[PDB]
Length: 56
Length: 185
Length: 185
Image 1 (cartoon, rainbow over the protein chains, first blue to last red):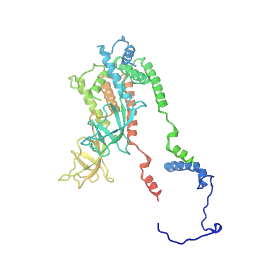
Image 2: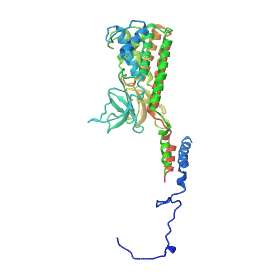
Image 3: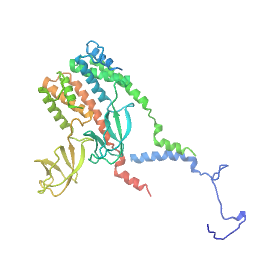
Image 4: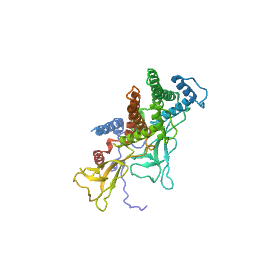
C-alpha cells in the first residue's frame, strides 16, 4: 500500500510508454499474432517429425 | 439357439434319429454336450465385442486378490507389469510374489450361456463339435468337406459382425484431437 | 482344464469309451497320463510369459550352490559366464570348477500344474499327446491330418497371446531415453 511519491505528468504526445498490437479485432483488448494464422501446419508437422524420429 | 437344436443337428449329421429333450438318456447326448461345452470355452478365450470389460480388484486382509469365477483369461493394464493366475489367486510375475499392496486394473474375458450367444457364433460352435465327433467316431470320410465349408462361411460372418460392432476409426487417435484443438482460436 | 477332460478327449480320439475318474484302473489311462506329463515338460522348456522369473542363489558352507527342484533350464546373467547343471549342483563351465565364491544371478524356467496352464497351452499338449499315442498304437492313418491341424491352430493362438502379454516396444531402448533427456532444458 505504501506510496513512493515521484508523481510525474506528461502530455499525451511525449509519453514514454507505448503499447502496441499486431492485429486487433474490434471489441477485444489484446491483439493477435502472425503464428496464430498457421497453427494447423505446425501441429501437422510435429507429429510427422515424431514418427520420423521413431523410425530413425 | 436352444441347446436341443444343436444336439439334433449333431445327431442328424451323425446319422442317428432326432430327439425331443436334452435330458434323454441316450449315451451320445452326453458326449455331444461335453464337446459343445469344450468348444465354446475354447472359442471365446481370445475375446470379442460382447464378452470383454475392464474391472478393478481389491486386496484381502492378508494381501491376496482373487479373480472372477467366470473369467477365462487375465491381463494387466498398469505400465509394463505382468499378471497371471495361480493357485486360485493372482500372481505378480514381475516381482515373484503373491501378496499385493493395493487395487489393480486388469482385462477379463467372461464365459456366457449358450443361449445368449449370437446365431453366427453358435453355428460355428455346433459345426466344430459335429466334425470333432464325426471324425473321431467314424473316420475321415468325404462328408467332412461340407462341415469345414459351413464352419468357414459362418466364421466369415462372425468376423464381419465383430468388425462392424467395434466401430474403429482414425479420428479417435490423439494426434487428430491435437490438430482439431490447434484449428481453433 | 481338468486332467479328466484331457483323458476323455484322448480316449474319444482313440475310439474307446469315456471314463469318470482319472483313478480308474484302465491300462490306457496310465500311458495317457505319462505321455501328457512328458509333452508338458518338453513344451515349457523354452520359457513363456507366465513361467519365467529372475532369482539369486547363495553358496553353502563348502561353496556349492543348489538349484530349484521345479526348474527345467538354467542360464547365466553375469557378463559372459556360462553355467550348467551337473550332479544335482551348479557347474561353473567358464572355470571348470564346482565351488563358487559368492551369490550369482540366473534365469529359471519353472514347471507348473496342468490346471494352472492356460486353455490354449492345454489344448496343444492334449492334441500332441493324442497324436503321439494314436500313431504308435494304430499306425499312421488318414485321421492324423485333423489332429495336426488342430495343434497348429492352437499354437497360433498361443503365440498371439504370448506376444500380446509381453508388450514389446521400441520406446524401452536406452537411445530413446537419452533422446528424451536431451529434449529437456
